[PDB]
Amino acid sequence: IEVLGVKTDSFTEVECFLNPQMGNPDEHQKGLSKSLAAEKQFTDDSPDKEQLPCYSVARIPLPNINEDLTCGNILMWEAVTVKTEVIGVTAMLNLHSGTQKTHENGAGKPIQGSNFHFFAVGGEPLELQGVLANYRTKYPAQTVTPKNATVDSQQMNTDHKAVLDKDNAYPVECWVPDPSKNENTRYFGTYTGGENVPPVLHITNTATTVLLDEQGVGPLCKADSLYVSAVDICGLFTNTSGTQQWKGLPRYFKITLRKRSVKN
Amino acid sequence: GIEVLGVKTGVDSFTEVECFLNPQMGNPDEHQKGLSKSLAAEKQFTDDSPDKEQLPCYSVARIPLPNINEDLTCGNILMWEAVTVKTEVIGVTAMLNLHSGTQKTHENGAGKPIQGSNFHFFAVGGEPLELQGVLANYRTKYPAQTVTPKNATVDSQQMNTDHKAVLDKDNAYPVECWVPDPSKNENTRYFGTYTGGENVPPVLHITNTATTVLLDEQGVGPLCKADSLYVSAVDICGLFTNTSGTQQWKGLPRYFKITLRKRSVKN
Amino acid sequence: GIEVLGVKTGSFTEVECFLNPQMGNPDEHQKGLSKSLAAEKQFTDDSPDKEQLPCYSVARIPLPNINEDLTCGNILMWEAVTVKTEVIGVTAMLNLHSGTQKTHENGAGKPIQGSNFHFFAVGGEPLELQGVLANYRTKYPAQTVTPKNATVDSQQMNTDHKAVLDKDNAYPVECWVPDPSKNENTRYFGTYTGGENVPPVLHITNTATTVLLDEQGVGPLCKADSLYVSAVDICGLFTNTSGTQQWKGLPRYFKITLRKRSVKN
Amino acid sequence: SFTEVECFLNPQMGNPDEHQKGLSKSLAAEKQFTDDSPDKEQLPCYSVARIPLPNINEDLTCGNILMWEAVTVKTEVIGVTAMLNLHSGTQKTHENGAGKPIQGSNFHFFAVGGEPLELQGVLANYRTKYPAQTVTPKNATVDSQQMNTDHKAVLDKDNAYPVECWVPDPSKNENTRYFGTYTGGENVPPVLHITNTATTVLLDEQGVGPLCKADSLYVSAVDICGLFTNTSGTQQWKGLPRYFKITLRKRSVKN
Amino acid sequence: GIEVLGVKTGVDSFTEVECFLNPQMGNPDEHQKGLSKSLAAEKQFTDDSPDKEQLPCYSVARIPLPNINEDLTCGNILMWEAVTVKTEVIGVTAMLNLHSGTQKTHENGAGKPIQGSNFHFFAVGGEPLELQGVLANYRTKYPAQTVTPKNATVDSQQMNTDHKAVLDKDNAYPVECWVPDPSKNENTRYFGTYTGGENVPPVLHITNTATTVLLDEQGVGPLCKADSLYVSAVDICGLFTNTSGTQQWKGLPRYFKITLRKRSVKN
Ligand SMILES: CC(=O)N[C@H]1[C@H](O[C@@H]2[C@H](O[C@]3(C(=O)O)C[C@H](O)[C@@H](NC(C)=O)[C@H]([C@H](O)[C@H](O)CO)O3)[C@@H](O)[C@H](O[C@H]3[C@H](O)[C@@H](O)[C@H](O)O[C@@H]3CO)O[C@@H]2CO)O[C@H](CO)[C@H](O)[C@@H]1O[C@@H]1O[C@H](CO)[C@H](O)[C@H](O)[C@H]1O
Ligand SMILES: CC(=O)N[C@H]1[C@H](O[C@@H]2[C@H](O[C@]3(C(=O)O)C[C@H](O)[C@@H](NC(C)=O)[C@H]([C@H](O)[C@H](O)CO)O3)[C@@H](O)[C@H](O[C@H]3[C@H](O)[C@@H](O)[C@H](O)O[C@@H]3CO)O[C@@H]2CO)O[C@H](CO)[C@H](O)[C@@H]1O[C@@H]1O[C@H](CO)[C@H](O)[C@H](O)[C@H]1O
Ligand SMILES: CC(=O)N[C@H]1[C@H](O[C@@H]2[C@H](O[C@]3(C(=O)O)C[C@H](O)[C@@H](NC(C)=O)[C@H]([C@H](O)[C@H](O)CO)O3)[C@@H](O)[C@H](O[C@H]3[C@H](O)[C@@H](O)[C@H](O)O[C@@H]3CO)O[C@@H]2CO)O[C@H](CO)[C@H](O)[C@@H]1O[C@@H]1O[C@H](CO)[C@H](O)[C@H](O)[C@H]1O
């Protein structure tokens, strides 16, 4: 999209709370995955959907701004800044409910281990690339995973292109944002691996991310729609029995937008 | 929110207020201030009734400010605007005591230092801090003398938008039940870091040279309603381990020094 | 050697590249992994297989020719100005169920972790290497380019060990490092972390850009209309149910912006 | 209008005997709250030195005088490489292995001011029976484990104020600049940087550095690097000297 | 000392020198260059006599610079001035060999990587680096062929100002005995980081885009006396662990790339 210079009614602000999609084994275990399996053979590994955390995504409708989309010059909503926040970090200070003792007489074991904290803001669905730890993994019916996985899907298999158009459908272990695309999206993620990794989570209402690219253009919202994507795997929760399930927390988005002139 | 006009400072347009806020970890008895009650583990999800003393709570103090004697009948008045804050965790060196009631790390070895999960948080606002409730266990039966999410549901372990509250009472709101609400708090600036893990080393910096500017994106700091300021804090440093192996949350006081200026607002 | 002149304005180009990792690939089914790793082999008889040895990844990217005559005193060359680069598939390691080893009874699988090395380079010619060995008496396998005539000093400085990254899946990571005494026409960046329990920390974003201009404002100049991207992304060790370990690698993406620069000829 | 003073400050870990300088006495554990009487040598203390400065005034009744003003400081922990000694009196990590390096809880701290550092007392155990030859919070109460504003003091004596009892007072210290970092945990790896290129500016928000009262400059330090583990498994704090290099300028003040 | 005058600019005013500095970890025999001798532990303070091969030493090289003065009988002269340095630890990827003489971490597992206490240090000066002696154990009986603090006393474990030296000899000054002296070194820039702990992960970055400026607060870089430049280094990466459990310090070479300019000075 060919963009024009900036104007100076011109602004709008939208909010969103996004629930995590860790699996939710039953009604009582929202924010969690099903117990995790281990030591499954590469040739016979069939994870349950509830064992697989998925990307969270919400399409946010923006106020109509064009009467006629055939006009040579139209206005689009341009995402300029975002404040974003992981919600409920203190909840993990509960070391008494269904926890596993660290030692005799001791407090319960805190949530810890591998984590992935990720967010994206774009004027389209996040564009994804497929990469698998095990290409022979038999993925459940209620998930969208890389079609026709091959030996190359554990490295680069360019055929595995997708978009994040469904909430609670695209497994995190299957997809990453595609850096060869996503011109109209800004995304940020950090993966930390290791069963003993301490979660480090910062909260504030003073941190802003500018969404303008190198030419000073933020994501341009197609069809007056804004897309917010998220993953916030905080780590593993350890049951008294020693079983473990992924723990996720909601993510808040506060996007500021401006009206931008574009060629049409 | 509140419509402000431009900045215009002269002589005696500034003021400075100080505050020491004690931690509210639980205080099992008079001899254990700054500590919680020993912590339980492995409680059934459907029958978990924590004691109030086991639950660290948010600290909050309302600081009165000098009366600017403004009559709220006119459309133009002056309000105190918080512009900067110096804040400090108090008594970090106290944890260098590894001999009092500690558990040795090994035979002939020194006592085990306070460590594990921690949460360090502070807020400055012209109103009480606005809170959102999130629970690890929505079926948790919280004690009478705590303010916790009302009518907790299945969704309270993720997003339940009904759980809105304000930090208006000290030693009442359990840290594990509440976080600052990012969808509100227009008139508050808050800052927090959570670290999880039983072996997490505390890292605490002290200095009198660090200043936090409280002005937002439009250059406006918290506007102090009713000539009052709110400071909030949590400083869970980690766990203290008793000789027996029992563990209790450790907290330290937090110091605030806020600088304010008179600002014109619409009324 | 090369004396630069003016830059063409108005003159730009962008090139992309996905580089597969070269960890060893023991068989068709195990790409991105090395072969089972050996330990405790004697110094005088250590003969590692090629599949046990991760290698440097490299791709030569062809660019358009800009000159009709190479006898002219002034000639145009492609100048790499910026690079966006990204490790691909970081989330794949959240698979803790496939062929993993339990951390405990009833527990999840052990995540990939341990020694890692993440490295990338952009240059107008192959990356220049210096050989250094942990064990100079190592018997390196066929189909690998390793330091020739390794001596006592190859465990420290042996300046005879000079090479160029001109072949993919051939130069073992453990034998070569980029040569800081050379590489005038290359920009390289690497981080080594050692320790069997080291957590991998991997960031992803499409908003991070590295400027490739040197102190004088000149980026890599692409000789023979060729751009070289080089990478190593050893993420750590994958632990099998049995406890056997193998290096894990991931692909790396490059997006390089180039401009036409006039140069003395 | 300028001057430069420099100082080396020995650590005050306790020094049980003349052969163990830089170390504390063996540390005790698992002592009762109501009967914990630590020896002075078991308690590391703040280091402090008053640095006399050239005299610049001849009449103190004047309404306008000159005071030395501290502008910058270069500071350095001294002897960090000494801990690469893993053979002397160390405990083996494993059969045939090297000795265990100093590690564990640490506290690195320095201050520059024109007065003694002002302290606030906070105690882990308010019922601790502190030994003679130490200055500790007087009349320690139930609230001394949190906020007890009666516990005010100044760092005016070297090897007297136990680190575990006192912190710099943020409600005061207008004429001092202090910086400290505490790390807790028995396995904490010491991380120590050295250079002669790092400078700290001591000017405050108004552009004024510490003003040296009575032509005196105070330098305060604590550098508990971690725990030294003896062969027997017995442990003692380890400290290192800190170097100060302060630049001062003449400033006019009301009087 | 040296009254510094104008900087020579433009044509024939700059030079560039490079250097690879081998590490001096001890070198037990010809097959173990880059390593120390197996390390001893639990030696009693009174009977501690370390071999030289067990003691990593500072690395140093004097780099001769082109003659700049045709006549040394002048009122003022030209000196080489070090302006910038690029420096690199060489061979970091060598430690990704976990199969040669290593100790497995577990059954069927890979070899234990090099890890533990590390010290990474470099210096650029127009003189030898000036050292202060500090000892962990002052009663340590240091071996022949090492320069260690003379007449070590009770105070050598803290501040003993008598222990002054200069790094004028390669593989002679034990790293555990000496640190750069911050009370001198006016004509040298030094940088080092010590990390202690037997499980500490080495973290080593490489690049040809990082430059350190050597100019001081006055805009003056090290002035090279007797047309000589001094590069100093220590790069203790950690401990190598043999199958048997014995451990030896590992070191790697360091590269230096220094840019110099001609400076006028009074003579
Ligand atoms: C070890 C134990 O059974 N603790 C239970 C505790 O019992 C009290 C005394 O224990 C300590 C401790 O936990 O080690 C002793 C410490 O010095 C105290 N620390 C401090 C800083 O004061 C702690 C601390 O006060 C509490 O834990 C705070 O909640 O208490 C114990 O010595 C004592 O036992 C004997 C006593 O020695 C003897 O003179 C007398 O004749 O009989 C006593 C038995 O009653 O009794 C103390 C009680 O007054 O009490 C708390 C409740 O107050 C808990 O029951 C605690 O057990 C843990 O409880 C946790 C949940 O709260 C969790 O379930 C753990 O698994 C339990 O071990
Ligand atoms: C220990 C075990 O066998 N777990 C299997 C689980 O069993 C369920 C209950 O176990 C817990 C647990 O894992 O500890 C109990 C916890 O309170 C729950 N935590 C939360 C936050 O809700 C978890 C959690 O709900 C699930 O793990 C999430 O998937 O489950 C167990 O107490 C219960 O016992 C029943 C018993 O089965 C029944 O015969 C008797 O009449 O009543 C008992 C009640 O006390 O059974 C629960 C299931 O009905 O079930 C899951 C499948 O839903 C798994 O089988 C799990 O075993 C692990 O499975 C992993 C892969 O999914 C992996 O293979 C591990 O190796 C297995 O241990
Ligand atoms: C295990 C042991 O006793 N080591 C002592 C060592 O013995 C030498 C050989 O051991 C190794 C080792 O430590 O594992 C073998 C490794 O492959 C070598 N590593 C490298 C990279 O070359 C190391 C290394 O060379 C040295 O450790 C460096 O000092 O040495 C050992 O195999 C050999 O023993 C047999 C030999 O197998 C056999 O063919 C022959 O017939 O008899 C030999 C017995 O002499 O001997 C090697 C030396 O000749 O030697 C050193 C001194 O040279 C130490 O004694 C070392 O023991 C440690 O000493 C430490 C202090 O230096 C400390 O006290 C530790 O507690 C001791 O274990």
Image (spheres, coloured by chain):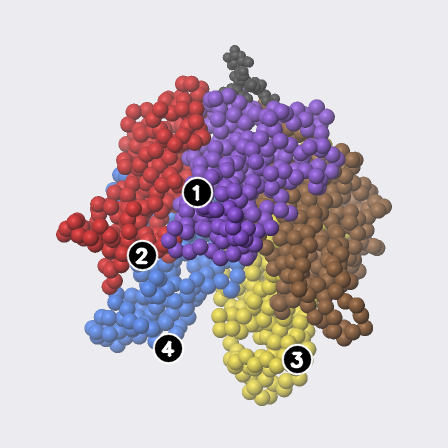
Chain colours: A blue, B yellow, C red, D brown, E purple
Tag 4, which secondary structure?
A: loop
Which of the two discs, 2 and 4, labels the residue nearer the N terminus?
4
Q: Are marks 3 and 2 on the same chain?
A: no
Query: Which is closer to the viewer, label 2 or label 4?
Result: 4
Q: Label 1 is placed on what type of residue?
A: Pro
Total number of numbered labels?
Answer: 4
Q: CA distance from mark 3 to mark 2?
A: 53 Å
Q: For the point 62% across and 24% down, which residue is it?
A: E144
Q: Are marks 1 and 2 on the same chain?
A: no
Q: For the point 50% across and 38% down, which residue is it?
A: E62
Q: Label 4 is placed on what type of residue?
A: Thr
| Residue E9, position as x, y percentages in the image | 42, 56
| Residue E13, position as x, y percentages in the image | 41, 51
Identify the residue under disc 3. Answer: B12
Q: For the point 62% across and 40% down, which residue is it?
A: E131
Q: Label 3 is placed on what type of residue?
A: Asp
| Residue B73, position as x, y percentages in the image | 60, 88
| In-image side of C131 versus D158 (left or right) | left
Q: Are marks 3 and 4 on the same chain?
A: no
Tag 1, which secondary structure?
A: loop
Q: Which mark is residue A8?
A: 4
